[PDB]
Length: 188
Length: 124
Ligand SMILES: Nc1nc2c(ncn2[C@@H]2O[C@H](COP(=O)(O)OP(=O)(O)OP(=O)(O)O)[C@@H](O)[C@H]2O)c(=O)[nH]1
Ligand SMILES: [Mg+2]
Image (tube, rainbow over the protein chains, first blue to last red):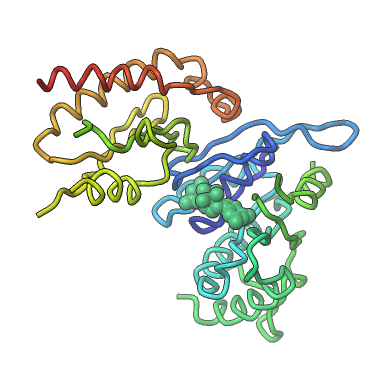
């Protein structure tokens, strides 16, 4: 089945997609449509997954996530770890909709939060990104202008979710995508 | 001077397939193209950046050029480049899988210089 890569513009979805499929680097520009290709997993049986790279632009992100969500075995939400500090709110807001969409599904897809661009010095760790995102989703479920996140009476945390949710670190620039290929293998 | 100072062809998926930026270098961006083609070559000229789409095979052609009034010649260069590119590489681009673009070699430089050198004669 399909693995959807989603995230804000410039989080690195297309470059990861390329790195996973060719092991190489390639110049890219902002994506305006989705792209897909078959990925042969690293494990013995070598199962095949269909990677689908979804544009992060606001005008297209939901239209396309809606179109492909029911076909998803897994969702990889990509995060620019170096720009995280200034983009936190935009990230949390998009992830919120991704969490909701995912839970409202018959067979909830497994979900990964790939903290990308680790090769850049100022990059926040996956541990710190998880912490700040929980704190932020915690405010959003109250301010957000019926499926809901965790329990209303307790501070939000990803573990309270009826979904498999993992965090890992990576870099698309060869690259450092070992953990990501491990996880992809594991969910195939 | 040159009819175009910048030219890049990428898929709508965001994959750059080929780009030109002088017989001098290999595309470092429109800004450097404006610095090298205009600033270091003399109101002064600006660089107009326009695009053309191929919706059937999901391609975007972006060109940067000087002198807004040469737009007709630039537009013809784009059309000729488009027609040739889509024929020479139809196999790599009609496929759905991105691997098809990822594994193709788009060595278009020579066919492009020819079309450029050729379009700069139609202008005269
Ligand atoms: N240093 C560094 N740069 C990266 C990394 N991943 C992507 N980039 C660069 O970041 C820019 C944006 O990456 P893309 O893959 O095109 O971004 P995207 O998420 O697909 O962006 P949209 O198509 O707009 O949704 C490119 O210049 C990439 O080469 C990374 O891990 N480290
Ligand atoms: Mg992209």
